[PDB]
Amino acid sequence: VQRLTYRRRLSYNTASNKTRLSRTPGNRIVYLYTKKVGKAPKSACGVCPGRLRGVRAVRPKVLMRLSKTKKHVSRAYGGSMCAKCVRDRIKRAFLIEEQKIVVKVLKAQAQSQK
Amino acid sequence: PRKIEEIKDFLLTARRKDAKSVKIKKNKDNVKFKVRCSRYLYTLVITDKEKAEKLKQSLPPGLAVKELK
Amino acid sequence: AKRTKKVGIVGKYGTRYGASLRKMVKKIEISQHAKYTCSFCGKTKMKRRAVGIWHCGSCMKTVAGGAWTYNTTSAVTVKSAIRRLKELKDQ
Amino acid sequence: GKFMKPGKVVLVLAGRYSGRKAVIVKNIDDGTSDRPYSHALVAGIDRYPRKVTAAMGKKKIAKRSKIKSFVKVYNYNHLMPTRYSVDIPLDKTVVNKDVFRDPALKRKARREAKVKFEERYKTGKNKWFFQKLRF
RNA sequence: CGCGGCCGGCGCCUAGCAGCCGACUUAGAACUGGUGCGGACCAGGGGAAUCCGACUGUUUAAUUAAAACAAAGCAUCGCGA
RNA sequence: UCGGCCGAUCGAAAGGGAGUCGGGUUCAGAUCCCCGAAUCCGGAGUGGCGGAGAUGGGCGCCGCGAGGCGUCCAGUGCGGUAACGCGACCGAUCCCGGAGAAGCCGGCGGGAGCCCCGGGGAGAGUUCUCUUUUCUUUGUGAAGGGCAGGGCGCCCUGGAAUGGGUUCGCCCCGAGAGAGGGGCCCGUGCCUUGGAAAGCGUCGCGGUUCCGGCGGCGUCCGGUGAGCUCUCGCUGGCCCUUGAAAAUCCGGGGGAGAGGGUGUAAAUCUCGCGCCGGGCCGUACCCAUAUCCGCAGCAGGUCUCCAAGGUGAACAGCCUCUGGCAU
Ligand SMILES: [Mg+2]
Ligand SMILES: [Mg+2]
Ligand SMILES: [Mg+2]
Ligand SMILES: [Mg+2]
Ligand SMILES: [Mg+2]
Ligand SMILES: [Mg+2]
Ligand SMILES: [Mg+2]
Ligand SMILES: [Mg+2]
Ligand SMILES: [Mg+2]
Ligand SMILES: [Mg+2]
Ligand SMILES: [Mg+2]
Ligand SMILES: [Mg+2]
Ligand SMILES: [Mg+2]
Ligand SMILES: [Mg+2]
Ligand SMILES: [Mg+2]
Ligand SMILES: [Mg+2]
Ligand SMILES: [Mg+2]
Ligand SMILES: [Mg+2]
Ligand SMILES: [Zn+2]
Ligand SMILES: [Zn+2]
């Protein structure tokens, strides 16, 4: 069968020297040098292990030529934090501030007695 | 390359300033109109022949109408 | 069927290293690789990540523990002692 | 008893308007065979009015006091109820449930909420409602 | 009436059938050759003991691969900056 | 006024690192030349064209209605319960986060290339007899669009013991199973633009001492798998071992500011198209029983990639095809 040769001068099976087989219109098999597999962002919460949705997974320098919509989600912290931990932060922010009102009122009615 | 879907988009594509030439390729099943713009080669596929002939005479003047047969 | 009479988990060591050394490492290797019930989420998924580091797969909570067990008997008495001294310190 | 009532301030938990403060216009809490879950018609504010100080000037203050609002129908599970309430008299005939089938009406209802919110933002009442939640 | 389609009075595969397609693998049997058949190739001689080193590992490139070194285990010593 | 890379600089032709592929062509060079299709980065001050922002309501009037005038008020986009989506989608200093950016081994699954099988062609081989036979060959690059396929620790309804779902193994569930309906990511597979005009296989006709010549026909339909090799993914195991850093790029938080008075409008634009540029050095060949080191055309030494048929457990040994050679 037809055996293949590298098309560049890097002769080692390093991480940057990864190829795939392609059949040309001239009916021959050649190496096509692939790009590395990109990763979606991880959530800024740093807790849940899944990667974000709605964001195209590319190499970091490819993000410079992508449009804005392809890199984020239409939500607060969208494209940086997951939906689940935004809901928890909204609840955590509101409930702690409500608690601050309680303790402020609680000591305010505690100081009515000398 | 870009594939132009309907007939009207091809007309103002061929009337662009950067349109160098239009090539007409007559296959067994369709007629392809390929206009060579600056960035893309826009191909319009016409299934029948009367519409292809009609489009041939409606092309803008002063543009190369090279026939591939 | 029960496959070994007494070696259990240290059957991977074969005839090597001595019976008492294999018996000694047997109870450590069992606790090292055991899955503990997480005290935060309630699931039995708290397993050792590295030496002294215990991680839960469900709530993704990481705890600093003992080398081979989730907590050491030394640290448990210490936590009880610190609690006792704290409640003695304040009044 | 039930607390999800018209006039009650809720916090939006999910969607484009996550973290926005909002007021319940009409609670359904039974389903309508098109939204079998418990939902509520909600008028909220998309853009909060900016902070205004004494050393700003009349024209700058009026520019910063503008409010961009929104109207939505939210599932209860995506709403965080609060203890606060505002007695803002939103026109029910303008802000109603069938406003979502015609964009022209949705603009009309969203305009109605905007003018009612802004005049209530003036006179310095319901100050917590018009402050952006920091999270 | 959209020799075909929307609902239904219109019936009991319910011990599961009908047709089509498909890899290799195992077991059993008969017959058979001048008892030869893992037919070339591939491909452990075995047992009973004694000494030393626990083992795996390493070593004098160019005469010594060992019982030598290493090793885990055991023990001792110094040290609070 | 703000401003700690808290330290110059060097250090990898196997680490990180945007973006080029197909066909043709030489005596010797081609991913570099030619042809054809793209693409990245940078620039545009006098703003290149569109599109977005962004062009709607209220009240007085005129007007048969429709529609026109004046005034006032908005207008830094919109949709979905949600996951999230749509072509853009104002915004600085500052802050937070992500990607870059991660070991070894196991077991599965998806995809491709190769191998195998059954037919249809074209050309060859055998024909002493047989053989509808044996052999060769029977394409579609990048980059776009669409659709499969794979994955999801993503969402909504709902609330499960007579526990159930489920893997080769596991494992999962009132912290929300099963079921129903959705969303996202990858998409190297298929179709399509590229594209048949090229390439190839055959059969011919002309010659330009040496034609990218001219022409006819064809480039088809299926089936298989613990197969082999790459690749993608899922899930485990091991560690007193936990398996780089930095350039570089991006998202978010915040809102200092900027933009116009209702105009065929402004600030602004990560949207479509258009315009210009990409300098320097390397590039032949050998890469070894003869181009390197060993005094030499020296049985030694010298880092890698590709990898067919039979037998067989097998990258074993033995025989063979492509390719190579002359002991
Ligand atoms: Mg490199
Ligand atoms: Mg392809
Ligand atoms: Mg020894
Ligand atoms: Mg010993
Ligand atoms: Mg040696
Ligand atoms: Mg020697
Ligand atoms: Mg001893
Ligand atoms: Mg340097
Ligand atoms: Mg060459
Ligand atoms: Mg094709
Ligand atoms: Mg479920
Ligand atoms: Mg052809
Ligand atoms: Mg070369
Ligand atoms: Mg030699
Ligand atoms: Mg020399
Ligand atoms: Mg020689
Ligand atoms: Mg000889
Ligand atoms: Mg000779
Ligand atoms: Zn999270
Ligand atoms: Zn836990």
Image (spheres, coloured by chain):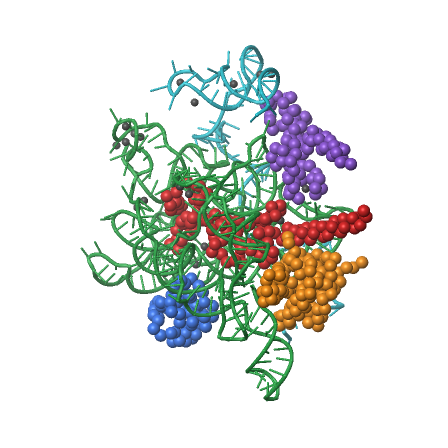
Chain colours: A red, B blue, C purple, D orange, E cyan, F green
Q: Position of residue D134 (x, y in %)?
A: 64, 54
Q: Residue at x 60, y 25 (%)?
A: C14
C20 relative to F42 in the view: left or right: right
Q: Residue at x 67, y 65 (%)?
A: D122
Q: Position of residue F88 (x, y in %)?
A: 52, 62
Between E61 and F204, which is closer to the camera in this rendering?
A: E61
Query: Is the residue D15 above or below the residue F104 in the image?
Result: below
A52 relative to F220 in the view: left or right: right
Ligand 6 quadrant in view: top left
Q: Residue furthest right?
A: A113
Q: Position of residue C54 (x, y in %)?
A: 64, 37
Query: Is the residue B68 above or below the residue F43 in the image?
Result: below
Q: Quadrant of residue C9?
A: top right
Q: Position of residue E50 (x, y in %)?
A: 56, 10
Q: Quadrant of residue F76?
A: bottom right
Question: Which quadrant of the figure contains the N terminus of chain A?
Answer: top left
Between A13 and A97, which is closer to the camera in this rendering?
A: A97
